[PDB]
């Protein structure tokens, strides 16, 4: 599993962070209150707790289930790019 | 005590909400995490837990100490305006 571009188009089910924390569901406000929901970002693919990039960070990310860690980049790398 | 204009200029010590809740200190991330701190909004007068309006809401406001109520308008009204 990997993302293309900056990962705005990523639509897989990867849901864990670079430090092995569990992503929080986008629809949930717990533990972290936020405004990155599917209503606010309808083009973001914000479903379940899957890594996404609705607001054009540099790569896919999520809020985390650790109350002390608001959000992290997900443990995904960019897919091999087209080479000449 | 009262505010002028939309209350961006309010610099008094009123610190309670329209429902009688206590304002959270601007520098604190508890109970509510936020980005309305004096470093982000240096022109906002964000000190202690006093009602302010750093981001041009319609009137002064604060985050609250009730974990279930993120922010409210403060219990302040507009000062009597200049009449012709
Ligand atoms: O938040 C933002 N703009 C905002 C606009 C209108 C209302 C509000 C809501 C304000 C509150 O409840 O704090 C109210 C209070 C009264 N006045 C407005 C916030 N923008 C924002 C910009 C950059 C970064 C972030 C943090 C964001 C996050 O950590 O959630 C990250 C996550 C990964 N990508 C970004 C947020
Ligand atoms: Mg790479
Ligand atoms: Mg009035």
Image: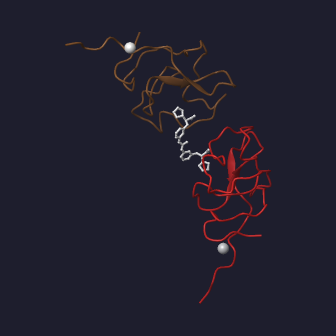
Chain colours: A brown, B red
Task: Look at the picture and state if A80 lies above or below B11.
Answer: above
Name the one closer to the observer, A48 or B5: B5
Q: State which quadrant residue A2 falls in.
A: top left
- Image quadrant in which the N terminus of chain A is located: top left
Give how far across and how far down residue A37 sits, in percent.
Answer: 51, 34
Q: Is residue A34 left or right of residue A11?
A: right
**Residue depicted at x 45% and y 34%:** A55
**Residue depicted at x 64% and y 31%:** A32
Q: Is residue A27 left or right of residue A3?
A: right
Name the one closer to the observer, B55 or A50: B55
Give how far across and how far down residue A9 sits, in percent.
Answer: 36, 24
Give how far across and how far down residue B11 sits, in percent.
Answer: 72, 63
Q: State which quadrant residue A44 falls in.
A: top left
Question: How many numbered discs sit on the rendered protein?
Answer: 0
Q: Is residue B14 left or right of residue A45?
A: right
Q: As drawn, which residue projects farthest toward the bottom?
A: B84
Give how far across and how far down residue A58 sits, in percent.
Answer: 43, 27
**Quadrant of the picture in which ligand 3 is shown:** bottom right
**Residue depicted at x 57% and y 58%:** B56
**Residue depicted at x 65% and y 71%:** B4
- Image quadrant in which the C terminus of chain A is located: top left
């Amino acid at each position: 599993d990997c993302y293309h571009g900056d990962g705005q188009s990523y639509r897989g089910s990867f849901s864990t962070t670079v430090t092995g924390r569990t992503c929080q569901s986008w629809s949930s406000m717990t533990p972290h209150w936020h405004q990155r929901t599917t209503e606010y970002y309808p083009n973001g693919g914000l479903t379940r707790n899957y890594c996404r990039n609705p607001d054009a960070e540099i790569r896919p990310w999520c809020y985390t289930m650790d109350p002390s860690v608001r959000w992290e980049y997900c443990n995904l790398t960019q897919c091999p790019v087209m080479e000449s």
